[PDB]
Amino acid sequence: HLPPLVPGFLHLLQPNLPIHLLSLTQKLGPVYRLRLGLQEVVVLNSKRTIEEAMIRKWVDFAGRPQIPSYKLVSQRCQDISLGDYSLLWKAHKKLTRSALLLRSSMEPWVDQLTQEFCERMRVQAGAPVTIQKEFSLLTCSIICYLTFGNKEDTLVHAFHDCVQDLMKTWDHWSIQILDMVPFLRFFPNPGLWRLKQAIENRDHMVEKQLRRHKESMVAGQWRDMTDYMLQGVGRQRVQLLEGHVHMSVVDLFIGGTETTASTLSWAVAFLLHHPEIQRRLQEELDRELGPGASCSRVTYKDRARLPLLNATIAEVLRLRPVVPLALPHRTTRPSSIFGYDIPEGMVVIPNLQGAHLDETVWEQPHEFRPDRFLANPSALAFGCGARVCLGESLARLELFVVLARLLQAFTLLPPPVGALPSLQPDPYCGVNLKVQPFQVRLQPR
Ligand code: HEM
Ligand SMILES: CC(=O)[C@@]1(O)CC[C@H]2[C@@H]3CCC4=CC(=O)CC[C@]4(C)[C@H]3CC[C@@]21C
Ligand SMILES: CC(=O)[C@@]1(O)CC[C@H]2[C@@H]3CCC4=CC(=O)CC[C@]4(C)[C@H]3CC[C@@]21C
């Protein structure tokens, strides 16, 4: 009783890994044991199994393996994501998550921060690279209501830059091999140096800030979330050590920026190929709950007042989920992940991307199809896990507020004498990437 084994030794190499983990499915089925690295890792490729070992069992495949690459960022140690399970992490998640849920509703700021962006782009009328503009749109936003609420392009462009440079340094064979070949002796490798050096800015920018927060403190929450966490820790009613706050900020402070940006960028790349969905959206937008051209409705309760949107976003998050294989889960108790018994400690890899192409539940999976509301099944882009996501709300929101006014203000047009991007890069890393388009950005309603 155990999942099958694929006869390979470095499946990790090879393009479009998510589409490959799917290919093996033709014979094996949803669950198969595979060697992504040098160790046999059990994958899952179906909305059913990837949900059974995530929601049903819950207790079992909830932890995360500590590989020699995670404890590299441990510092004092502990935190969201990388950190393993343990009762501390549980209470650690609940604290840094309630912050994102917050007398200071983050709803308004988001809808405003994006407006400034529209104008900033509206003055361009040229061919700005969307990736940075939006890749900086969210940064200008998570930075306002999470750490000292600076928002200033002086402290934002500094934190935003720390994000991108903190990614290509963690997701590079140079630093990855260290995990596959631990016995390596860690002969000096160039990548490790570039990481340790860039990982400091991430530790420093939070240390120099967390202090200002410490002193400028009052009875409740300061402008930002830091004041909440940095306070909701030194008052625990009985671990949750002070250091935890330093890390909790990181995921959101410098983690919020990349993931959501990619989703937004991907969506734009799709509308470029489908003008149909673009204008059908422009009409369904104002002729649905926005008879005007601005500052009218466009929110939460209304959120239903916009069908094509709640749909378009659902597709983009299903065809190109920003995080595809999500993160590696580890088993704590021997349990069955379906079909076959699974040994404890076994690293589980929930193939989200693949489960989204299950043609047994989603029709014409490969085809951008906005339509689904009526209704079509749900697609897990944020996982469904005791780890689920810690900011699924913030994310889901930005994709609504940003896209909404993105269409209304501008046309969304292709670069001059250029080809539209798409299809997905082979250098798939922690978060799924995108090619570099140059969308035009104009409209005169
Ligand atoms: C809509 C864009 C996003 C997508 C598709 C996405 C997807 C995911 C996925 C698949 C995971 C791993 C789930 C697991 O395997 O257990 C994850 C984890 C996480 N995400 Fe996101 N995410 C998005 C946006 C965000 C944003 C904007 C934030 C910042 C508030 C965020 C913060 C996190 C954190 C902190 C974790 C780690 C949770 C843990 O402790 O396990 N995500 N996300
Ligand atoms: C148990 C082990 O030997 C490891 O922890 C050491 C190397 C780990 C790779 C690292 C790269 C990677 C990136 C992803 O996004 C999905 C998960 C994998 C494939 C992950 C699987 C578990 C591996 C193989
Ligand atoms: C998009 C997502 O899923 C996340 O935002 C949720 C967890 C985030 C980890 C958090 C830990 C970390 C520490 C660093 O110093 C470098 C950046 C990472 C690897 C960072 C990458 C983006 C991730 C994976």
Image: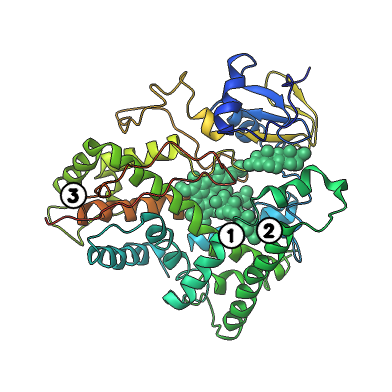
Viewer-side residue, 116 vs 87: 116
Numbered-mark total? 3
Q: Residue at x 31, y 31 (%)?
A: 373
Residue at numbered disc 2? 79
Instruction: Rate crowding at label 1 as few (under 14), some (14 to 19) or many (20 or more) other CA atoms within 10 Å.
Output: some
Q: Which of the labelled discs sits on residue 251, or is there none?
A: 1
Q: CA distance from mark 1 to mark 3?
A: 35 Å
Q: Secondary structure at mark 1?
A: helix
Instruction: Rate crowding at label 2 as few (under 14), some (14 to 19) or many (20 or more) other CA atoms within 10 Å.
Output: many
Compared to residue 139, the image places residue 310 above or below, namely above
Pointer 1 residue Cβ closer than 8 Å to ligand 1: yes
Check disc 2 and give the amino acid type: Asp
Residue at numbered disc 3? 289
Q: Residue at x 79, y 37 (%)?
A: 345
Pointer 2 residue Cβ closer than 8 Å to ligand 3: yes
Instruction: Rate crowding at label 3 as few (under 14), some (14 to 19) or many (20 or more) other CA atoms within 10 Å.
Output: some
Of label 1 and label 3, which has the lower sequence position? 1
Mark in front: 3 vs 2 = 2
Instruction: Residue 317 in the image: state x and y as whole percent.
Output: 43, 40
Q: Residue at x 56, y 42 (%)?
A: 427
Check disc 1 and give the amino acid type: Asp
Instruction: Residue 170 in the image: state x and y as whole percent.
Output: 65, 54
Query: Would you say residue 389 is visible in this rendering?
Result: no
